[PDB]
Image (cartoon, rainbow, N blue to C red; front, top):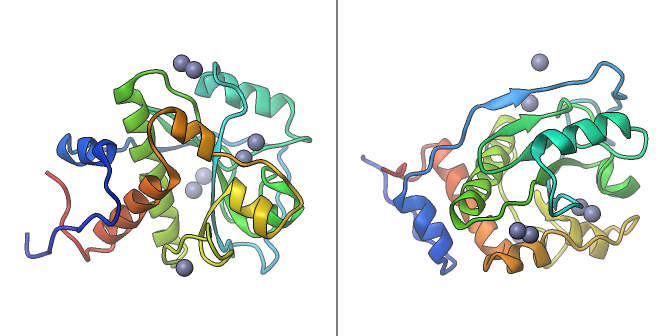
Length: 207
Ligand SMILES: [Zn+2]
Ligand SMILES: [Zn+2]
Ligand SMILES: [Zn+2]
Ligand SMILES: [Zn+2]
Ligand SMILES: [Zn+2]
Ligand SMILES: [Zn+2]
Ligand SMILES: [Zn+2]
């Protein structure tokens, strides 16, 4: 195409594998629940400020199990979306907040969960799927990707970054989870950034 290829800012054999395989994220599915609460973000309904990277609390759950448990326990916690190696499922409308990152995170950011995977390919697909969903939301909300990890400013936040800069929570996901699969947030962010650039037609698509 007329567009330049993205130059990766982070060395990543897993990202290389994703790009070379030309992985295609699945369609975003809606699975909403009538009794979930619908409250605006701190700047209003329809005004999220960014997106949070979570991994699921359990290492052995399925996306279906996670969702069923959440519907039963929504007064304790619920999130906007789950991704695994096969599916992207939005469980609450992104124009309203969700209950996944403590009081301060919840007022600002879309909460997205990475379901755990147990093989190389499934893990790589789940990373592609998270990154694709995140880039889609940033594009839809006219937000630009900016990692908050080191200075507490921007639109892409790990739960760890929320804990560090905002408080109201102490979870450090997804760092240890990604490390256990020989990956990292730095690599995930580089993938989000590239996918955002592809979607906004600034760099060439894969193929
Ligand atoms: Zn709908
Ligand atoms: Zn979390
Ligand atoms: Zn495991
Ligand atoms: Zn949506
Ligand atoms: Zn495993
Ligand atoms: Zn920045
Ligand atoms: Zn957690």
